[PDB]
Structure formats: C-alpha cells, structure tokens
Amino acid sequence: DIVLTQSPASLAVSLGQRATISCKASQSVDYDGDTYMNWYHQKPGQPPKLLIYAASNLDSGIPARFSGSGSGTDFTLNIHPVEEEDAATYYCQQTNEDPWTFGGGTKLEIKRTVAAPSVFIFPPEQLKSGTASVVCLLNNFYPREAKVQWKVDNALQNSQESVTEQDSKDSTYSLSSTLTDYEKHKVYACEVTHQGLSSPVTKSFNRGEC
Amino acid sequence: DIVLTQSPASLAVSLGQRATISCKASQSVDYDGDTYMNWYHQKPGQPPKLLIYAASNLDSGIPARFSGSGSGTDFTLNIHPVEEEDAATYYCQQTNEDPWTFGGGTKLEIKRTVAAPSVFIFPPSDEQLSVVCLLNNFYPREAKVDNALQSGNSQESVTEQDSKDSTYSLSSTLTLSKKVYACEVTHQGLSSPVTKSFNRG
Amino acid sequence: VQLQQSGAELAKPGASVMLSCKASGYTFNGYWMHWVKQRPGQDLEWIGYINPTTGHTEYNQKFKDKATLTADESSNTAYIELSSLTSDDSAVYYCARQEYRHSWFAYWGQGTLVTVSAASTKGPSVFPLAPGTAALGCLVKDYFPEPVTVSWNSGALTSGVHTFPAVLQSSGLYSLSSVVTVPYICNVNHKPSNTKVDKKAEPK
Amino acid sequence: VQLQQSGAELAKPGASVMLSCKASGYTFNGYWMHWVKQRPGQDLEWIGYINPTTGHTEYNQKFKDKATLTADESSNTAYIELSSLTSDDSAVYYCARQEYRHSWFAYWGQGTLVTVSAASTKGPSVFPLAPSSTAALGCLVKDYFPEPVTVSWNSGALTSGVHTFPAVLQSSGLYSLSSVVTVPSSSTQTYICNVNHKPSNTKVDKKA
Amino acid sequence: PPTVKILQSSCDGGGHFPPTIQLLCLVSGYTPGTIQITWLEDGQVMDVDLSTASTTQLASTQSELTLSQKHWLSDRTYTCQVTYQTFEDSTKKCADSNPRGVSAYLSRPSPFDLFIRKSPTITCLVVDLAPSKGTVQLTWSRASGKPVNHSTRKEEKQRNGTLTVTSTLPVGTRDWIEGETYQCRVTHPHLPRALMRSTTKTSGPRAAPEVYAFATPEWPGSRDKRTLACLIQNFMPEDISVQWLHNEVQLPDARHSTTQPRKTKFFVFSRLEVTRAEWEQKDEFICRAVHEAASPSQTVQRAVSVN
Amino acid sequence: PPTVKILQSSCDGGGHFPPTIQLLCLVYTPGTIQITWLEDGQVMDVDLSTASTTQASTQSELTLSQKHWLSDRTYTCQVTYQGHTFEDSTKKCADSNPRGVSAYLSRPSPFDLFIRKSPTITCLVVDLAPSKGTVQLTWSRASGKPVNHSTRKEEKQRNGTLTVTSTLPVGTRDWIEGETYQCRVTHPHLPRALMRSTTKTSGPRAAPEVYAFATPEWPGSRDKRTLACLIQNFMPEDISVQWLHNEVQLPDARHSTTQPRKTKGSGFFVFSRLEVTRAEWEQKDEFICRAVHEAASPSQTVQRAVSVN
Ligand SMILES: *[C@@H]1O[C@H](CO)[C@@H](O[C@@H]2O[C@H](CO)[C@@H](O[C@@H]3O[C@H](CO[C@H]4O[C@H](CO)[C@@H](O)[C@H](O[C@H]5O[C@H](CO)[C@@H](O)[C@H](O)[C@@H]5O)[C@@H]4O)[C@@H](O)[C@H](O[C@H]4O[C@H](CO)[C@@H](O)[C@H](O)[C@@H]4O[C@H]4O[C@H](CO)[C@@H](O)[C@H](O)[C@@H]4O)[C@@H]3O)[C@H](O)[C@H]2NC(C)=O)[C@H](O)[C@H]1NC(C)=O
Ligand SMILES: *[C@@H]1O[C@H](CO)[C@@H](O[C@@H]2O[C@H](CO)[C@@H](O[C@@H]3O[C@H](CO[C@H]4O[C@H](CO)[C@@H](O)[C@H](O)[C@@H]4O)[C@@H](O)[C@H](O[C@H]4O[C@H](CO)[C@@H](O)[C@H](O)[C@@H]4O[C@H]4O[C@H](CO)[C@@H](O)[C@H](O)[C@@H]4O)[C@@H]3O)[C@H](O)[C@H]2NC(C)=O)[C@H](O)[C@H]1NC(C)=O
C-alpha cells in the first residue's frame, strides 16, 4: 500500500495570485520513464473532475490556469490566476501500484471583499403540526464567521444551524438557524452580529400580528 | 559482409520423402534476440518467392510441409512430405546487416519411377531450303541422342524438371546446310535403343 | 459518454445490498469499471476493479470480505454487493471507468447514497416560509433516511435559490430548508419514502 | 501490389542504360525498393535500396561505382542507371520491394535481362515443324539477337503440354530456340506459334 | 448491366464514429426489370428488417443498411447482393493505416525447473491487449500431435491501461529434452488473422559456464550492509538460472538484481546485498548456476565471504 | 432552413482504400443556394467539385486523393442558403488502436560536458513508416535566442522501421545555467505538431564508487582473461564509463557495459565487462576503469587500476 499526503489541508487565495498545493507519496510512482499521478477536484454534491494527468498534462476543456509539475515523489499543482468558481476540494492520485490510493484533499476558500448578510425571519400556518419552529436566514455574506442569537422576551435561551458551501458565483456563504412553550411567550427576534455590519441588526415580530 | 554457405549444392529426394538443406553463416544472424534469416526458392524464368522468414516463420500461403529451424550460425529447412511441385533452387538470405547476402543455392531433384522419352524426327522446312529430334517427358536427364555416326554437327538443349510431371525434355538440332536422315536414342528406362527416320522428301 | 448510478438505499445491519452503474455509448476497445467509497468529509478509498469483458476481479485487501464486484457487458451495467454491513460501511459509492491506454478515471458516476440503519423510512413534512428585494422559502423537516432533494417549480425559479445541507435533528431525523430572493412553488422529492410534495411560496 | 520492369535491352560496351520499375497502386506508409543482380546461373547478389519518399540510398561496396539508384515518389517508379557497361554486366536484374516493418522481401519484379555486346539487333527466323504421325508439331526460332524472344501458342489458347526450350548459341554468334507442344493423334484444329522479339520490335507467326 | 457502388456514413469532425453506421448501396444504370436486393454479413444473409429500399427509373435503386457501432467495427465483411435476372460490392471496416498490432512471446523452461526441480514448464504470453479482446484464447499443440496436459491461463492489468494474458504449459521431463516443438495459437474475434508461435530446445553448441564471485570493499558509510557480485560468462546457450544461497537455502529473486544474457565477444551479472546479521549467522554465500552443459548434475557454484 | 450531411466512399472488402475518396454533400424552401468546400479552413478550387440540383435537392461531390484523405485533413461543406451560412465537417475515421509517434531527447554525456567540455544534445525519433521520412523536426530555444546548426540523418533498422536522429550542439555555459530546449516535429500526415523538452538534472547528487576485479586463470582460456568493473551509488543516472590501458582510452565498442538501474536503497549501479588479451597484459599489466559524473570529485573523474597476476 502506497500512502499519499497533501499539503496544506486548506488555504485561501485571492483573485489575481497563484495557488499552490503539493502531494508526496510513499513510493516513486515513476515506472520505465512514465509518471502515474493525477489531479482531481470535486464541488459539493458532485463527482470529482480531472484537471491534470500524468503529473504535467491537461485534460480536455480545462483552462490554461491549471498546470502541474513534478516527478518521483514530489508533485505540484498551480492555479494562476484563480477565478471565482475554483472553490473545491483537490485530490492527488497514484496509479502505479495496486491498490490505487488517493491523497488527503485540500479545500480551497476564495478570498473576496466583505459582505453583510441580508436578514429575513420566518415564523412557524404550520402551527397545526403540534410544534413550532423559527428560522432566521443570512443570505450571501462573507466571510463564513457570523453569530446568531435568539431573544425570547428579549432574553437568550435548543437551536441547530447549517451553513451552505461557498457559492461559485456570489463567492459568499449563507447560514440558517432553526429555533424550535411557543404560545406562552410574546415577542421573538433574531440577533445577528457580523463583521460587515457597522451596528448589530435585529429583525423582530409579534405573534399573530396583522 | 556476412556470407552464407548452404549445403549441399544439389540433392535428390524420392516423392514423399524428407528433404534437408543446411545454411551456415560466418556470423550470428541474430540481433535483439531475434533471428533475421529468410528462405526463398526460385522457379525457372521467375523471380524467387519467400518461403520462410525469421527462420522459423512461414509466409502467407505456403504449404505446411516446409519447416525451418535454427538460429545463430546454423540453419535448416525441412520439406515433408515432398511433392512434385517443389522442383526449384533454394536460396537462404540474411537481413541482419547491410549488405544482405544469399547462399550458393541448393537444387532439389524429385526422384520418381523411370520414364522413357517419346522420340520424334522432324525433317527441315522447305522455307529455309535443320533436323530436330525431340525427347519429351523422360527421366532422368542422363540421355544419349546416311547411317553416318557423327559428332560436332548438332547442338543440344534441355528443359527444366517439370513442376507437375517431374520429368525432363531434350531438343537436338542436326544442321545440314544446302539424302537419308535419322536419329538414334538410348536411355536407361528403355530396353534397347530406338530410331526415328524420315525421308529426303 | 456519462455514467448513471442506482438510487439511494437503506439497509439493516448485517444484510446485503446491490448497487448498479450504467454506462452510455459504446467503446469497442473496452473499459474497466472501478468503485470508490467516500464518507461525506473523508478521503477517497479504492475498492477494486472488474473487467466486464472477461469478468476478472481484483480487490483491495481491506474490502475482500465486504465487497464483491459483478458486471454484465450486454447492457453496459456494473454491479457491486456489500456483505455484513455496519455503521462504518455506510457511505457514498462512486463508479468510475478507466479507458483503454489510460491511467486515469475519465468518467465518474453520479454517486449512490447508502445509509445503514435499523430504523424504517420516514417521510418529510414541507412547510413554506412567509416573510429592494424580499425573500421566500420552504422548510422540509423531520425526514429519514438521507437524502431528500428540493427544487423550485421544476426549473421555473433557478437563480437565487439556496438549499442548505441536511441537519440531523436530535430526535434522529434530518432537517433542511430552501430559500429564494425575488425583487413560486417548491418541489420537494423524497425517493426512499416514495413521496413527492409541492408547496407554494405566498404569504398566509 | 505488382511490380513490372522494363523489357529486354541491349547496350554497347562503355555506354549507359537505365531500367524502370513501377509499382501498381498507392501505398500509404512507404516502402524500400531494392535491386538484385543474378549473373547467368550464379549467385544472387544484392545491389542496394532507395526510399523514394526522401531519396536516401545505401549501396554495396562492389556496385558503388557501377549502379546509381533514382526514384520519383509521385509515379511510384524507381530507376537504376548502369554505367561502364561490360560483359560482366550481362545478367538478369530484378527489382524487389521491402514493405514497412518487414525483415524480408514482399514483392518481386519480372526482371530486366540486359545483354551487353557489340552485335547487331537481329530479328528471328521462324520455321515450322511438320507432323508426320499422340501427335507432335513444333516451331524453330533461328538467328536472332539479342535474347530473349517471346513465344506463344495459338495466341495463348493452348498452354498445357508445351515445352519452350532455352536458347542455345549458334556458331555464328546467334541464338536458336525451339518450342514444341503435344496434342491428341487426331490433331481437327489449328496450331500456330507467335514469336515476339522485344529488342528489335518484330513479331511473326507461322502455322504447323 | 447494373452497376453496384456502396457509400457509407461520414465520421464526425473529430473522427468519431456515429452511434449507427449506414451502408448505402447504389445500383444504377440497368435495363428496367425484375431485381432483388439482399445484404450479406460475412457470407451469410442478413434479414431485411435492417434495410429500406427505394426504386426509381435508365433505372436506379438504393438500399440503406443500418448497422450499430459494435457491428461495423467488428472487422466483419458486408456485401450488397443484387440479383438481376449476380452482381455484388463488398466493404469492411476501414483498417488502420499504421496499426500497432499484437505481439506474443513464448519462452523456454528454466534449467532449474528442468534439471533440479525436474518440473519444466513453458509459458505463452500476449501483451498490449485492450479491455475487450480480453478473452483471447491460447491453445496448445505439438509438432507430433502427442497429448498435452492441462494449461493455466491468467490475466493481469498493467499500469499503462493494457492487459497481458499468460498461459503456462508443463512439459514431460524426457520429452522436452529429445527435441519436441510446442505451439501456441492465439485467436480472438476482433483479431482478424490467427497468430502462431512455437518453441523448442536450443540447437547449438554446449559450453559450461564460468562462475566468479567477488565482494565489494568496505565503502565509507557502508558497514551495516555489504554488496556481493557474481559474474557468469562463456556459457552456451543463453538458457541459465542464477540463484543465491545462504545457510544452505535459496533466496528470492527480490533480494538480488540479475542482468539479461548478452552475447560475449554469453555473460550475466547478478548483485545481492546482505545485512549485518546475514553474514554473522553463516559467513558464506553460494552463487549457484544451473546450466545444461554443467557438471556433475548441471550445477556449478562458487562461494563468497564478507571477511 | 436547409439540412446538410456528408457521405464518403466505402473501403474495400479487405478494409483497403480506393485510389481516390469521393465525398458527397447532400443539401428546404427553394430560393438562393450555393455550396462551398473548405480544406482545414482554406477554400478549395471549385473545379474539384461537380454540383447537381433537382427541383429542392442539391448535392456536390468532391474527389480527394488518398494521400490527403489519410493525412487527417478536415473538410467542410459550406452552404449559404438565401442569407446565412450552414456548415458540416468531416475527417477520416480515427483508427481504433493507433501507434502514434515516438520521440526521445537525450541529455549530454558527462564525458562531453565535463571531460571534453563540449556537450551535445539529441532529438531522437523511433519507429515510423518510410513515407514519414520527410518528417522535418525543428529546434528552438526557450530563451528566444537563435540556435546553431544541427545534423540530420535517417537510418533503416532491422525490424523494417525508420529512425531519424538529429543531434544539436549546445554551449557549455548555457546548459548548466538551467536552459530548456525543445524539439518540434512536423509532417503532413500529422495534423498537429509533436514537441518534447529536456533540461539539466536538478536534485540530489551523489558520488559514484568503483570496484575493479580480475578473474582467476580458467583452464580453457590460456591467452585471455576477463576484467569486470562495478559502479554504484551515484545520482542521478547521467554517467559515462571508459576503460584505459597504457595511457590511452579503449573504444566504446571494446567493452560491454549496461544501463543504470536503481539500488535497493540510495543510488544506481552499473556493471562493466572487458575482455583483454595476453599481449595486452604483457605490455602493461594495468587497466583503469574511469567514470565521469556530476558529483564525482574532484575533477568529475574517479578510477582504479587492476592487474591480472
Ligand atoms: C505497457 O506495460 C506493460 C507492462 O506489463 C508492457 O508489457 C511488457 O511488454 C514487454 C515488451 O513489449 C514484455 O517483454 C517481453 O517479455 C518476454 C518474457 O520475459 C519474461 O520472462 C523473463 C524470464 O525469462 C522475466 O525475467 C521478465 O520479467 C522480468 O525481467 C525483466 C528483464 O528482462 C525486468 O525488466 C522486468 O521488470 C521483470 O522483473 C519477463 O516477465 C521476453 O521473452 C521478451 O524478450 C524478447 O524481446 C527482447 C527484445 O525486446 C529480446 O532480447 C528477447 O530475446 C526476446 O526475443 C525473443 O527471444 C527469446 C529467446 O529467449 C524468446 O524466448 C522470446 O520469446 C522472443 O521470441 C520481452 O522482453 C513484457 O513481458 C511485458 N510485460 C508483461 C507483464 O507481460 C507493455 O509493453 C507496455 N506497453 C507499451 C506500449 O510499452
Ligand atoms: C525496431 O528496432 C529499433 C532498433 O533496431 C528500435 O529503436 C529503438 O527503440 C527504443 C525504444 O523506443 C530506443 O530506446 C530508447 O533510447 C533512448 C536513447 O538512449 C540513448 O542513451 C542511452 C544512455 O545514454 C544509450 O544507452 C542508448 O544506446 C542511446 O544512445 C533512451 O533514452 C530510452 O530510454 C527511456 O526509457 C527507459 C525505459 O523505459 C528509461 O529507463 C529511460 O530513462 C528513458 O526514459 C525516458 O523518459 C525520461 C524521463 O525524464 C527522459 O529523461 C529520457 O530522456 C527518456 O526519454 C529508450 O531506451 C532505442 O534508442 C531505439 N534505437 C534506435 C537505433 O532507434 C525500434 O523501437 C524497433 N521497433 C519496434 C516496433 O520494436
């Protein structure tokens, strides 16, 4: 068994510079003048896609920014210049000796400008289900770091959050929070503090108001 | 300049027997682990055709009686069983290095049951005013062609061993520039010599 | 030129399942079919390969007791069976194909989400999200097993749609939500439960 | 995949002759075409080859001054020009062809017989043979130069049982060839031999 | 007198084959009358459910044969048969202009398996074969036709995306030495022409090998391990088996690196490296050579020591 | 709206081609229409085609020579119908398993760069057909500076293949500076050009080691003895070996040396064999096995002597 190792595990590159990732193996994947190392990358939910094969050859329909180099046990991939749709997880692969094996993987975050999240709130019609839930959405914000706190009667208290992947077009993340005794309290609010906000913003609503 | 020396230069094999020809070389005809030795045979009037290449490979459309073996400096060609159509001269060739060179040749003769010639005397044509004594389809080639036993007033000509009858034929031209003409013939298959005679008219 | 995998699966611990992979077109020189296991958030593992033209098999030593490959060239379909399933065996299974004179995967499969659980299938409940540009969304909570997918009007509203990854609720069921910004109808599909629910985005 | 060469030729000592060898068809990958000399009843001697695509050549040490290979790619034709013709040059000349990825010869030509002498080009003399009584009739080709002569029976209608004897040199320095053919005793039909002498461009035919 | 000509579908702008190849047979310029159109695949009749015909009137007629990519590329022969009161035109898959082709090798038994182990085997090998063409059969036959034992067949996927089929045939101990020749027949449907290869015991002189063992001096920094070398030269012919023995037992091939026989002006070099604990147990290593011309029992060896 | 598709000539029953290749282009609302052929983009002589129109049905047949059809040229049927253009293309059907071209570019031998100080590189092309003998390869330097004059020669091999070898001299200072040279190969049969680059070896460099031996006297060779030499543990693989007797160098054809191969640990290794005569050792019982290497010290030369008695 050959063991491959990539470095780093994650990095953030801005638009206009070159990204660089290396991958080292337990054996020389060279053989009789040929080198058997490839470069894949996959976006969330999708199967991987080949970018560079044989350590220095480009596949069909791949931009000229992606290039590789190396031999023996050291290999290197470059992305110059980086575009907005390059955020993915990149893998190296060896195909010289069974069993075939892959590298660890290197996640790519796109460094862009600051963006404050647009805040919307949604109350539970669905109240007939026997239990209520409050969802607060933060759409198209950067970076991923953001805080959300729930105010029940203007007081903090059973919440789970999810974050979408970095978008390929907007290059921004999005966050959701599900706040699941409901009728016993009056006012609900979603407190969000973000680096793009000069002042902390909060959206509020009263139950059955209209 | 690799030279090839094949032996023997002439041999006779019975019909259905086994023919063996050796081809010796001055240098290894092998290179890169492979043998560059070929085998051809030449019919009269025609160019040679390839019988076996790389010593141990038969060409497309060659009978299964031909088999070649050997490498390095000594090679061998085997024919079994021999048929009447194999009457030709065999040459071995090397393609190992320039210049390509052939052997001395081996003439294979197909032995068979002895046959007597059909003798005929032809008086000369009146358009010239040249006797012709024909012996057709006999075997073997050992033959002896005014009641005057002469010598030096006639010429000879012989055909090749036929490819389907395996027999020879001979032509004799007794010349007479401007009354009794005849031709005597003695052969091994015949019991006693026979004569064909013709008129002065 | 592309490949087509089977649908999502749900299996009990210790049983066996069958997964497929369909190849398009025709290649007269042949091909090799490989299987690659991956848990969401883990490195890629090579299970093995099988030559559909001859049926020959070679397995990773760590998968010889768990995986056995099968293929039928009459329909360009590749199969794989997993025995003695545990919680560590649940993952997503890609099928990749190696072409002739190639040493790289040229075509990948869509991926088959397999979950090993003793619990039965549970259907989702879809609730809308009622609120210059505003937003509208839909909430699909409490479903099992993964995954369940959602869309907006079957291509009517594509841009501005954000559907977050599934969040495992503490009860044992999953939960997800989709939104859309407009300055619409939600199409929620859950194949393991054989339930397709539609929901419109309008205030109420 | 056939090779046809020039016909018979005659040359004076010290002159030059060029022999052609054209290949039928278009072969994509290319091919080397050699030339092989065969003296009267002696060994097969190798001369050299030429790649018509580029014109590169390699000659033998013996024929380096006697032969010159030329070729044109467009017409699939090769040429060999022999200078300083001598009696040693009176021989049969074949053009063999080696194909791509072959350690041997694949196609051979019919051969171009070259006779180097000072004798005059002479037409043949055809005299029939009288059948007197399996019947037999023949034809006599006398006093022709140079060799060879093309003989055909019934313009190619009768080919079985025919014997065309090799030429023999007469005392006056001229050639003589004979041909016979055997037919059933009834014989009903006609038997005519057609003779062609390529060097002198003469063609005759006589009846039995 | 009808004229028969066949056209076919043109390939893609990048040379690709379409999903379906279409053979259009054109029979034009015949006196109007009764006429029949039949398609023939490799000599046998194809059913008319894959063909459509169109007739107009001189007189000309066209029929379009619809084949799949697996059909036309199967290297088969198709003939448009027109029976007019028999005229025909044939076509097959356009062959490669520079085809790589197949190569096959058939080696001879090792002198170790022939003399010491006394279980000699020959092996037939085909390399550079596609995924398909992977059931290519390798059947055995002898020059005399005498029975052969069962043969093994194994296939191995290579690094360059190729496949190699291997077939090993055991031979009788006395039968191989007298001079029998064994044949290997390679055939597959895609492969048009059968490939044939044979082997036999070498027919040349016989000369015993000269064995010489030596040890490399103590190189700076190389005290925990030592390099041993063995030179074997002037043996005929090139069939030889080189082994290394330590503590009166043989070592695997992976421990040493041995060259291939090259012709002498044959000689081989082998290189075995030992560890510190290797010579401490038994400070003696035997470079054993198995050759047909050796004596007493087709084996000649020499020892070597580290100190 | 017109419709356009092309049909070509079918191959012989044995998969062979006709002498020529004919391509028929079949073309809707009647009006203005005209057909044009394009050879890899360039327009062709309209005299090469013969058009036909039936009212509508319009077609045009273009006859190609097998040389150009097999040269992998792309041909386009350009049809302008009552306004705008519509195009269909076609090239020769690709081979199933082709052989392709094979090219090699070698590094200068250390004896030329270090001992003689006049290195040379070479662009080698192996295994191709005779008609691809006119394949002209063109040198080029990555720095943009012009290249010196090179040598070209074609060679007829045993296996009936051709080999065109092109040697290029280089400047000593330029090579060590880390230059990259490229060989560009062109031929009408290949629509695209093949290129390959080589440069100096950069990486860990280790010094070679020499061990010489003289075989004992064997009973059957009274007047001959074999000399061996083992070189090992050197990086990288670029090296050159020579034998010396009586202060002169023996030709390369005098000793049978092998190609480098990696050791079980660090370095490569090479064996060498030398057959000298009895008169060779009686004149001077001394034989040197020298080697030129990058990391060889001091002057890139290391050798040892050996005697037979
Ligand atoms: C894609 O990759 C694959 C990798 O699998 C390549 O496949 C290889 O292709 C090569 C050549 O195409 C094959 O080599 C042939 O092997 C024949 C059998 O040899 C085997 O047995 C010997 C024991 O005798 C083993 O030691 C060998 O393996 C080991 O040894 C070699 C050193 O030799 C090491 O380098 C290896 O790493 C191994 O450790 C083999 O397994 C062999 O007979 C044959 O040799 C003929 O040709 C050479 C010149 O090339 C001659 O010198 C030689 O003499 C042979 O020629 C005739 O003469 C002998 C007389 O003894 C006859 O016996 C022969 O039959 C022959 O008629 C050749 O070397 C290799 O086997 C094969 N690999 C496998 C696994 O099958 C593909 O080529 C590659 N594709 C491309 C496009 O490159
Ligand atoms: C018909 O027969 C002919 C010969 O009769 C045959 O041509 C030969 O083909 C082979 C294979 O294509 C050629 O071998 C190559 O030769 C080059 C050049 O080597 C020179 O230099 C060495 C050492 O200096 C000398 O020993 C040699 O004699 C030459 O002078 C080699 O460089 C090639 O080696 C490559 O492959 C090896 C094994 O795979 C590797 O170990 C080696 O490192 C080389 O690897 C490649 O990649 C490296 C990666 O960086 C790169 O740096 C290297 O430069 C290299 O590109 C190879 O051995 C041989 O030269 C040909 N001979 C002639 C006279 O043309 C035909 O192939 C044959 N046809 C058929 C169909 O079989």
Image (cartoon, coloured by chain):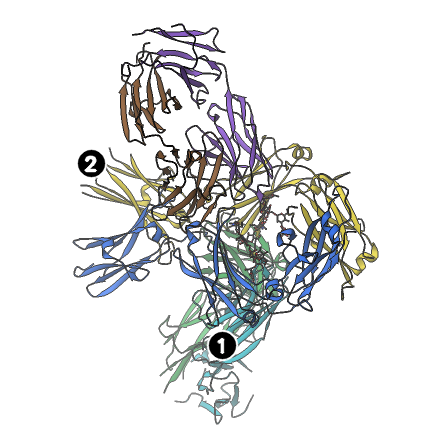
Chain colours: A cyan, B purple, C green, D brown, E yellow, F blue
Q: Label 1: chain?
A: A
In this picture, is B159 found above or below E246?
above
Q: Quadrant of the C terminus of chain C?
A: bottom left
Mark 2 Cα within 10 Å, few/some/many (few <14, many 20+)? few
Q: Nearer the viewer, residue A196 or E144?
A: E144
Front disc: 1 or 2: 2
Residue kind at label 2, given as amino acid type:
Gly
Expressed as whole percent of the image width and height from the top left, the position of residue B139 reads: 47, 16
Q: Label 2: chain?
A: E
In screen coordinates, is C147 left or right of E176?
left
In this picture, is E17 found above or below D162?
below
SS label for mark 2: loop
Ligand 2, by image quadrant, is: bottom right
The residue lying at 52 percent from left, 38 percent from top is B101
Residue sticking out furthest to the bottom: A199
In screen coordinates, is D164 left or right of A20?
left
Q: Distance from label 1 to label 2 (Cα)? A: 74 Å
Q: Nearer the viewer, residue F31 or A195?
A: F31
SS label for mark 1: loop
Q: Nearer the viewer, residue C151 or D194?
A: D194
Label 2: which residue?
A: E33
Residue kind at label 1, given as amino acid type:
Glu
Label 1: which residue?
A: A165
Q: Is residue A76 visible?
A: yes
